Amino acid sequence: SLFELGKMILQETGKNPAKSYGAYGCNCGVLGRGKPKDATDRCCYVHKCCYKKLTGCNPKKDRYSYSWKDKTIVCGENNPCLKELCECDKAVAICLRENLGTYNKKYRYHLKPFCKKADPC
Amino acid sequence: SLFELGKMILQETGKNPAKSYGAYGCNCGVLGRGKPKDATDRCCYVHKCCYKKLTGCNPKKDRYSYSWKDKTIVCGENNPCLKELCECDKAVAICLRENLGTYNKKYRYHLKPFCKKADPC
Ligand SMILES: O=C(/C=C/c1ccc(O)c(O)c1)O[C@@H](C(=O)O)[C@@H](OC(=O)/C=C/c1ccc(O)c(O)c1)C(=O)O
């Protein structure tokens, strides 16, 4: 769920996940994908393609267990959907951290009509 | 869909919808409902209760047609769900404009633990 995803992003990036990634570029935040604006945005693009592959669970509401061991996100699920969902969320948290260096606040609150159509996943 | 909702909010309030309302108080944003902090937050509370009684369509993803006639949102659907959905979104956009006078930036990125449980819809 968003609770786990938000905590992962905080633990990896150190940033308030709502402030930094709740509305960034064409892919970080609500409703759909668009052609990514930069590497941070592309992380959220991959994350949304990751969610589309899920079958049998709801990525927004379904909770799962993970732990923070050796400063690493360690998913703690056997259920295939919950396990894949947790790895989707872990991957975007890591990707956002890796690309913090090119984060540009000018892409915060980017408007949808200014995004081109995204490619199929 | 959130596309139409965002456009209505922009047309009514003139404000960037994600900036002002993507994470405000306990109810504006993607964290469920909570006891509203002020009138703007109450608009979003009412909006989410409105979404909860929709049957037959997906409020986040289902796109619909409306018109901007004499600076009024005019819902242009007669399918019952899309019509109701359009009316939910129109009402929150108008409500948010009507309560700009007490909008308080201090409620941006309000932390969920400070929210109290919402009353039943
Ligand atoms: O539909 C929209 C906007 C939707 C939307 C917005 C914010 C949100 O947060 C959201 O969720 C949705 O805009 C589209 C529409 O008006 O029909 C359409 O606008 C235009 O073409 C405007 C062109 C133009 C304007 C000013 C000028 O000076 C000029 O020369 C040209 C387009 O941009 O594609």
Image (tube, coloured by chain):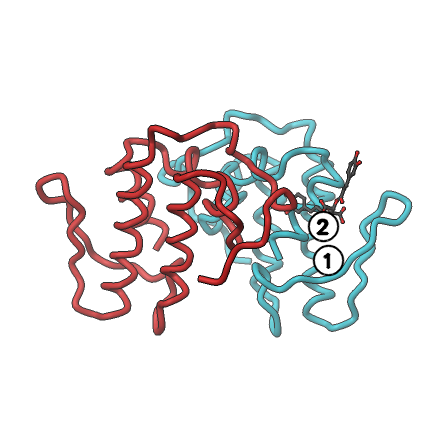
Chain colours: A red, B cyan
Residue A64: image location, x then y, percent: 25, 59
Tell me the SS state at disc 2: helix
Residues at discs 2 and 1 in contact (Cβ within 8 Å): yes
Ligand 1 sits in quadrant: top right
Q: In the picture provided, is A33 more to the left or to the right than B114? A: right
Residue B25: image location, x then y, percent: 50, 37
Name which residue type carries label 1. Glu
Q: Label 2: which residue? A: B91
Name which residue type carries label 2. Ala
Measure the C-alpha gap from mark 2 to mark 1. Answer: 6 Å
Check mark 1 vs ligand 1: CB closer than 8 Å? yes or no.
no
Q: In the picture provided, is A17 more to the left or to the right than B93? A: left
Task: Report the number of numbered marks.
Answer: 2
The picture quadrant where one finds residue A76 is: bottom left
Do the residues marked 2 and 1 share a common chain? yes
Q: Crowding near pointer 2: few (<14 within 10 Å), some, many (20+)?
A: many
The picture quadrant where one finds residue B111 is: top left
Q: Label 1: which residue? A: B87
In the rendered structure, the residue with mark 2 lies on which chain?
A: B
Residue A82: image location, x then y, percent: 26, 65
